[PDB]
Amino acid sequence: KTNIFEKRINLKPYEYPELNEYVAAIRHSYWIHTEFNFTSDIQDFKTGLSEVERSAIKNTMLAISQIEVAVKTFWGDVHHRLPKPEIAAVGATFAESEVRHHDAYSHLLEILGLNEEFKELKKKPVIMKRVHYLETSLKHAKSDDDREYTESILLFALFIEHVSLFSQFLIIMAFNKHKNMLKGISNAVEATSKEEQIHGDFGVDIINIIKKENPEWFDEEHNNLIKEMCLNSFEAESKVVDWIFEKGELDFLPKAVINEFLKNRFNKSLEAIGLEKLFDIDEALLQETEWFDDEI
Amino acid sequence: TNIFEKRINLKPYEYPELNEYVAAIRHSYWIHTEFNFTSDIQDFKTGLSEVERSAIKNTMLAISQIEVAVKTFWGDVHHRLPKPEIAAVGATFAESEVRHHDAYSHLLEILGLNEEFKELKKKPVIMKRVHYLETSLKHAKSDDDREYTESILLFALFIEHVSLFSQFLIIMAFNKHKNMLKGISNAVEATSKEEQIHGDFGVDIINIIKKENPEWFDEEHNNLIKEMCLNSFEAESKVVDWIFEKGELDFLPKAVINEFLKNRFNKSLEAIGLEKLFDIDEALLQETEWFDDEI
Image (cartoon, rainbow over the protein chains, first blue to last red):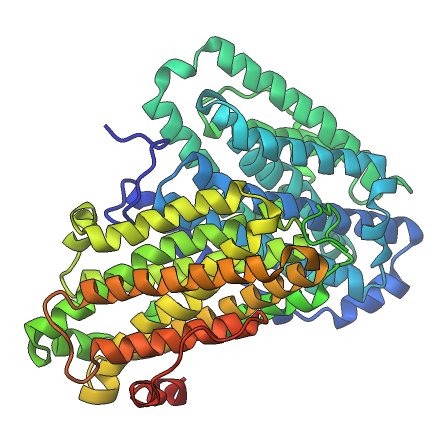
């Protein structure tokens, strides 16, 4: 008789006690940027990096920080659609973790002398288009039918948190891997990724609950709509990657390699919710980022 | 600068002073697992009378359930004050309410009082308060900006600085007067520090709204707030009667709790620039001077 969409006022008993484990998971992964040491990173950025490298780092941290503001809102609003106190508890715990994250990356931009980047956001059409896309998506996640709600969860929890943000974490961590630079920032990125992993995992679980409770909504037509949405998301993400590298590609982490890493994570997101892979993976391009998953 | 106007870009903050509240909660952050409730379980089972057990049970049920609504309020503030720095505080506060409701539901569980949540619908006094906050969450979402200071006043002050503080007082009175519930008293102290911060933020944002929109706050509006405060006090006194449905605590009578409430209602009105409403009985108020001395 359990219906994830039906409001329950009383805190206990939980109808989904297994989902409560996500609150403990984030309490375990909890971190603030002040736990890390960025002193050497500042000098690495200001003296060690090339103009092309500085620009890629600056654009990546601006993209992470600003998008996390929207991801926070998504999680803080989930209870409006899935009005269960235990789900609301996860949502609030996740929203606060996004604030710790956006504070970390805005702090890094500040200490690197890159504060002006947020003021000029309106003048960066590629990243601002992504910002508006998420603002529009937050409106849809609030007002669209329950039948379509799995698409809002898929967008934020998977396509943004498990896919888009992971490619950005990959970009930053590649500096430590290939150049032995930005070690402190790489530690903060690793701490961020562990929390984003948890977020997407919860997104997978709630999509699977919705599918289990409402099997009639998830027909062949629905699966095709998700595949088209995934292809649209990839095309949009590839354009975000092109903007990150507007001043030039990193020879140690080319765009083709980042794009293959994205396609593979999109495939894993589809598979997690019971759908078939969409992208035919180039194993040589994918092997180039195997170190990332081994590091996490 | 307009607190009600959406700003998309994270930085620069328009209200950088409000950001300090994020650091404040990160400093006060706690989980119930940091405390030891072994001695408390024993006090509840053998040290407390049936009248005392009932007051503790009702108080923790009231705190835990109301914290679920307070969490939602903070998580929704961004919808009305769409500034990323305010949204950051709101999310940080909403998560602190989850740590709090987890602490009190855990305490109810370990004391063998789990069935209390199942029977909420059958407790009209506390359930009326529950529905009042659900209704207030709808109004905090949809009413005019002109009235938004009343939603903040209700949740951040009348609930977090007043109602919940009387409930913290009830529990902490057992440690003060009977040297019992020491572990629970430590958790209540940790909760109170975070609720203090929440109300302080509520005062700051109400004061910003008043400063930016002075024309809304005329003599008629100030009288509406005073009437709302009187109504809130009358409603709170009924919640106190229900907490003590099995009988009053001789060491903390209802008259003393009610005077503590009136004094905190006065402090909340004064914080937002209004005059005191209640003419305080100093003998009744003196009885709870220890509480502020403890925290």
